[PDB]
Every structure is written in structure tokens, then in C-alpha cells.
Image 1 (cartoon, chains in turn yellow, red):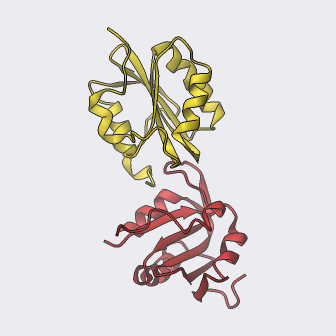
Image 2: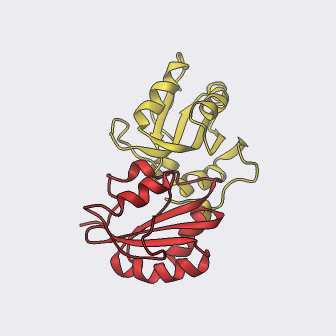
Length: 128
Length: 118
């Protein structure tokens, strides 16, 4: 067993795969170890003043999903993540299907561990 | 060709770009077609008791700008507007600059709720 080279297949359809793109987004997701996830959970929340950020169980690892106040290039959300994150796999990408990504993160095979707004988000709150 | 994805780059600075927020505001702006813009001018005026609302010529399309006496979630405004043409609804952070820009070439006003605007 090596480390994931990308997010689980189930989610791939809701994410952008141009991690080098110059496009900017406000929704992001990170695939990394449990311990790092929990740490990036507090860090990212502060760093980008997230409007929402959730941590999810994902096959022995974790997935952070978060919404930002401003727009950024997946490029800079990755540099920051990596910075404080050696010796640990870390996969970062922008989300195109915001609601779909999160909602899927609340259902099997996934499940929430914690989230900035207990209660979670509903589809109509999104302004894609 | 696909419909627009954002407001004209020349205005992005004055706007809020969260696709998810619990922040409420009293100034919004909609980027859609000329016909939809017209419908909405009246509809939006009534629905949110705007204190001021203006509709400007963008290029092929139109941009609607208004201020509210009370605050709402951009999402709530958007949900209302959506109910087939493209439509982009967003909060405005720098209200004056935003309305000012919409009154200069390229842009111009078609109709506003206050003679002279701002």
C-alpha cells in the first residue's frame, strides 16, 4: 500500500485536474493523512478565513473541503499546504461541483468528522 | 459560444466572489441579458424594497445594480432571480465605484430609480 496519487475515484467528477491552471476558485479540497488533515483544518481556517471547512473520513485518510471568502489559484493553496506538510502525501484541487463534492462527502463511503458550521450546508446556500 | 462566466473583468475588483457565504449585504449586482434585466428591474425593485436600482448597458447584455434597506444573503437574491438565459448575481463591496464604473464608457445607464443616480 502506497499513498493515494489522487482523490478517490468517487469524487474525481466534481474536481478540476489542472492544478497548474491560472484560474482562481473559492472552493477547494485536500487529500492527506488524518493527522495532517486535522492540522490543516485549523491552519487553513485561519490562513484564508474560510466561510466553511469540513474534515472527512476517507479510506484510512482524510479529506478537507472548504469554501473561501476570496478566490485563489489551486496553485497557492497547494504551496501553503505543502509548506507545513513534509513526509506526508498531500493532494490539492479546486472544486467545480461544490454542492456535489460536499454532499458526497457526507455519505458512504465517506462521513464527516467535524465542520466549521455544525448542521452542514444545503444546496441553495451555494452561489456557483 | 458559451454564455458569460463572470462580470466584465473590468469590474471584478468591486465585487465579492464567494460561492458560499453567511455574510449578508445591502448592495448587489446582476449580470444577465437585456430582456431579463428589464423584467428584473421591476421585480427586484418590489421584492427587496430597494432604495435605489439602476440598469446599465453592458455590451450585448446588461448589468443590474441596486441597494437594499435591509441585508440579505447574495444566495437568497440569486435563488430569486433564477426562477433559461444566463444570470450572474453577486454582492458589491465597493458600491460607489461599482455604480460609477457602470456609468462610464463602455457602460451607460438605461434607467435608474433615482433621477441622476449617485
